[PDB]
Image (cartoon, rainbow, N blue to C red; front, side, top):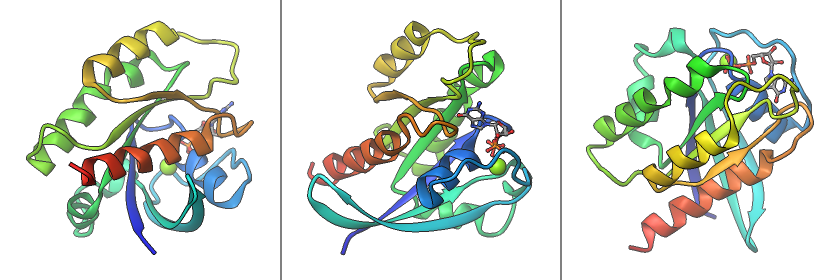
Length: 169
Ligand SMILES: Nc1nc2c(ncn2[C@@H]2O[C@H](COP(=O)(O)OP(=O)(O)O)[C@@H](O)[C@H]2O)c(=O)[nH]1
Ligand SMILES: [Mg+2]
């Protein structure tokens, strides 16, 4: 069966680890070592196709590790994550998209913009802002909550759909 290599990137503390653990293990972790970068694997059914997901949950401390460049070169799709209560994390998104495009040496890279923590009442990044950004990038935008599981499957599954279309060119 097809294996899709997904990489989750974003500013520290936006919920990259919580989103992945919720997707893989169906539970909300409220504190996960922020220096730990690992890979998680899950078999899922997306649009009737059985496939395997290999997800890399990046950590900022591990960026200049020997394996980061391998997982970056091997990654087919990227989840660009920000938190809706973190204005700076949203403002940083452009750096991550630029880095991925630079490494892939490609303008068109399968990507999805994710606004995490949508369960929280305090929101400093409005949905209109993220929608405008994703539309200018030509990528989907999905609101998620690792706590309540809202949008978690949709975020990862859409990235898989983005990967499939890129393959069919
Ligand atoms: N309320 C809420 N808190 C979250 C959500 N996602 C992550 N968090 C919390 O935000 C903090 C940082 O999460 P973490 O996964 O370690 O972020 P990371 O540094 O990107 O890996 C942790 O305390 C999480 O419990 C969410 O969807 N809702
Ligand atoms: Mg983490």
